[PDB]
Image 1 (cartoon, rainbow, N blue to C red):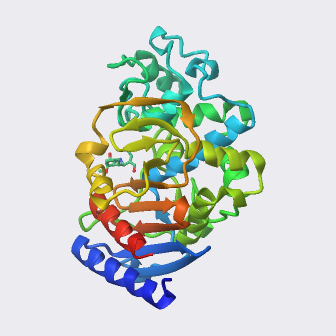
Image 2: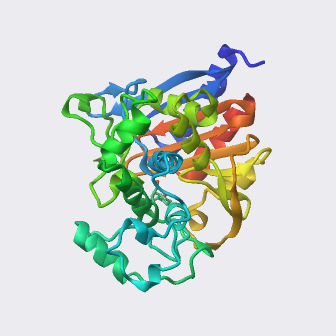
Length: 359
Ligand SMILES: *C(=O)/C(=C/C)[C@@H]1NC(C(=O)O)=C2[C@@H](OC)CCC[C@@H]21
């Protein structure tokens, strides 16, 4: 098999050149292999302070936060609280606009509502304005025909999905996903006492961190360390090991195939491609020109339950952070790459593929 010594060389020889080429200050990596996570840390979390990256350093996950959103939703579905086939309106009777008529919770969850934009406008600062926004939105496409990557879409699915529980989103997440999985250093809002662990992001020489915004916890506001993230990946890769019945089901639902777009399949948060898949196919869908383009979908009805022979992944970025996670259930291997610099997505998947290919 692969030796620990060999794995360390593979990780160092892949990660060290990447950091130098992409000028990334710090990086924390976890490689899941043979039932155990292996940690590798590099560089700095804060240049000014000269603080090294450690397995406790907190990185902004950006869109990888959507995997937590998906699982939390799947768990609510498994509890009988929500259904993906339900009209959005069942959860928001105030959304009276007739354009929402045939739009389901599935569409919000999978960016398939019909043209919801990338971001919730900055002018949207509260509930009543959020209503104004969706109420005046005019869909470019009919529901279930076009996938357009949007925080305005999945962010609303997140808010609405926790409504029947009676709990605010943050408490629903902590109570039903984070605490049971022992993700004690995973935060939507980082306490004052945990702040010294929070790395600084770096853009083009400026120290940066994520700013607030409507539906941020649902779409891009989660921060964690590489330990919690490795254990999160391990729960999603092997949910047979998750004791909570509905949480086990929610994990499955988030890795289920709802739509096919080219060579990939849309889940709830997670995205998948059939394994074996070559690097060039994964890398080519990594591009922003592609990731952000509106594309037609082929519906999978009924949705297909998780398939073990899959490359499941998700990229995430904020102004100062660049993260990526990928695992193959069939092979029980996975990788987590957290970084305090948003470097090119294709570079992320290339390195992840190369090291996983070594296993
Ligand atoms: C998820 O990480 C995410 C939310 C939409 C990040 N948004 C942005 C952005 O700058 O608007 C990026 C881009 O990386 C350039 C494009 C894909 C999504 C991500």
